[PDB]
Image (tube, rainbow, N blue to C red; front, side):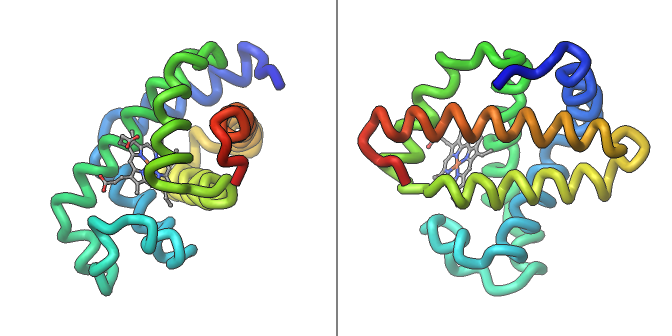
Length: 154
Ligand code: HEM
C-alpha cells in the first residue's frame, strides 16, 4: 500500500503534538494496551508483576520504555513509507527474541488510536484517524512480511 502526501501530512501533524510530551503519551499508550488486552503484559518480564493501573503509572521503568517505543515509531513514521532499514532490526527482535505476534501489534495500534483521539480531538477527526490507521496498517503489513522472511510468520 501507498499513502498519499496528504495522508502523511495528517499523520505528521498530530504526531507533532504527541512529540510535545513523548513520555506522557508513551505511558498512556502502554497502560491502555495492558488494560484492554491483559495478555500482552505477559510478554514483558520487566513489567509482569505490576498489579494495578496505579502501579503502572508510578513505574519509572514503564515510562522509560514508553519513550523508547514512541521514539522508534516516530522515526519510522517520519520516513513516510521509506522505512525498510528501520524496520529490519525491529522485526528481528520482535520475532526472535520477544516473540510478538501480529495480533498484538494490532492491539497496540488500537491503543495508539484511542489515546490520540482522547488527547487531540481537534487534530484527530475522521480523516486524520483514517490516515493514521492506514500508516499503522502499512507498518504492520511490512513487519508481517519481514516476520515471514525471518521464519516466524506469527
Ligand atoms: C508500535 C509497536 C512497537 C514498537 C515501535 C516497539 C519498539 C520496541 C523497541 C525499540 C524496543 C527495544 C529494542 C528491541 O528490543 O527491539 C522494544 C522492546 C520490546 N518490545 Fe516492542 N515495540 C512495539 C510493540 C510491541 C508489542 C505489542 C509487544 C508485546 C506485546 C512488544 C514487546 C517488547 C518486549 C518484550 C521488549 C523488551 C522489553 C525489555 O526491555 O524487557 N513490543 N520494542
